[PDB]
Amino acid sequence: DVNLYGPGGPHTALKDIANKYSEKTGVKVNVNFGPQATWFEKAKKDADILFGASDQSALAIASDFGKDFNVSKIKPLYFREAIILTQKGNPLKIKGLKDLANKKVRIVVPEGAGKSNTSGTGVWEDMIGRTQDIKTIQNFRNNIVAFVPNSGSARKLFAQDQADAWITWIDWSKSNPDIGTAVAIEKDLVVYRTFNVIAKEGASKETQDFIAYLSSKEAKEIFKKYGWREH
Amino acid sequence: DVNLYGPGGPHTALKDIANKYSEKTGVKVNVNFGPQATWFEKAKKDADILFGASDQSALAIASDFGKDFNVSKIKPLYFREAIILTQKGNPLKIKGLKDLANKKVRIVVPEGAGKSNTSGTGVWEDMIGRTQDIKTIQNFRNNIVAFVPNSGSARKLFAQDQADAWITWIDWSKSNPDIGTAVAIEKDLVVYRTFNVIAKEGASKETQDFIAYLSSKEAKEIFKKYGWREH
């Protein structure tokens, strides 16, 4: 078996890819996902590949594994853009990030706060900071009602109508057409973060084979369906 | 005394400001700075103000203090641009981030890896990611020879000539004009991160007065000298 572990997000593309791969090759590929704490102990025993939803978070998670993984071997393969997810119908008529700074809105964002490894860390400030206006930065921050440890937590909060806007990734919207309404972020502000993988030291032939498959034509198309790009 | 604690970087502006403030008011203001671990236990006793070199790192550090500080009260006041610091004279003629990706060069970047709270976390990927080209991202990352826990560590590594380029902030160059040559980052890729402060719960009038001073015309001018903007 080839066992993958990583955060929620890329798991939807990976599940599809793994399904197709397993049927085609006979090799069983398992995609374990969620908050790091839910799978960390198990991963330490049988993780073949660690996948990531950003570089900083992947570096963090792989570093928790010590000798089993060499962090220098993290492989970026795709990227996707940040988006604003609004409640269905976008009742507040949010047009972008600047709009979120100037209106009265409840925003949720994943931030690790140094105790959780999440793809969201640093995202909101890097985007709104590109307005080069401290008042705008202050205004946006004042609207953040919740910093959460991971995207799954943001999704739950959002689903309970506890926030008007969730700063997230396009793939979360693609994976969940039924949840909210995606609003594109200003081209001059938006950030793009990567999907990546790292194989354990002494990875099996089956593991190496699947890694290659992630760059295959079939994999590219599935990734594309969820918003993951190469160029 | 009014005691401030925070990371290296903003400390140079703050020390100038604190000196000027003390000269004017007679209130003694101490600026403690460095890797969090070096002052954490002391700060637990007498920290009046925590200052930060980015939002994500400030959120992390303030969170570590539990009930002593209310993280919702973090105050962004200034921002500055990331830069590339090259060895003095810029021998490799580095022209920006894309140039770094294309050339064979050794890059140092501060990344917390989930175990250190540093202003650098997420910066390099957010900038190079805006090229929207996975090969460029891959190439850039392949040139990173060291992910260090804080900017002070990057400075030391850089000073030892163990890296050709250090992804840092303009203020590090302004504070250390002689240790290298600053190269501006492409305006369409660069990120800007903030300086912030948070006063302890039950902060004294004198503590509050100094916080106000950080927005005074005198303080603004000192911040500006080190590259901190509003504006």
Image: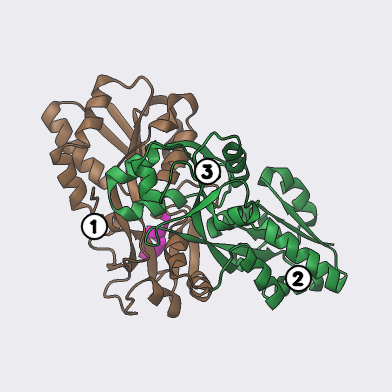
Chain colours: A brown, B green
**Secondary structure found at label 1:** helix
Left or right? Give the position of B212 relative to B89: right
Which stretch appears magenta? A152-158
Q: Is residue A147 above or below residue B105?
A: below
Indicate left or right for B174 with B89 as reference.
right
Q: Which mark is residue A174?
A: 1
Residue B137 vertical position relative to residue A4 in the rendered view, above or below: below
In the image: residue A142, left or right of residue B202: left
- Residue that sits furthest to the left in the current view: A24
Vertically, is A59 above or below A185? above
Residue A52: x and y in percent read: 36, 42
Query: Residue at image x 56%, y 69%?
Result: B229
The residue indicated by pointer 2 is B210
Chain containing mark 1: A
* Residue at 64% in and 65% down: B225
Label 3 crowd (10 A; few <14 / some 14-19 / many >=20): many
Read off the residue under disc 3: B114
Mark 1 crowd level (few <14, some 14–19, many ≥20, 10 Å Cα)? some
- Both on one chain, marks 1 and 3? no
How far is the residue under mark 2 from the one under mark 3?
32 Å
Residue at 83% in and 67% down: B22
